[PDB]
Image 1: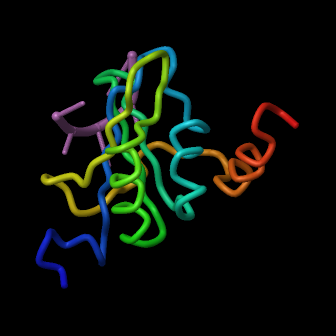
Image 2: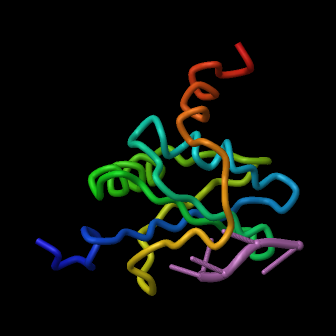
Length: 112
RNA sequence: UCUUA
């Protein structure tokens, strides 16, 4: 274990291909939550990229494997979720809303 | 593609 990067005591999962003006916290996490509980997330509207932190490394690999064959489409752009090669941990420099509520958002689908 | 324009 811990051979393929130190994604255990600290995980960085990077999501990309998010359009500026369309990089919402809810949707990025909407991808995260159904495969695993989202503990942290970071949206970088500037680089059209984002970070998604998950409860277990198993979730990170699962999402990557899924979106490799079935990508997430935002504004007609396929999102690419991958494990970051440069960073081991995500620290929230910017605060966010309750992520559990985002689970309710996912279940609501289109504001049920 | 890699800390929030």
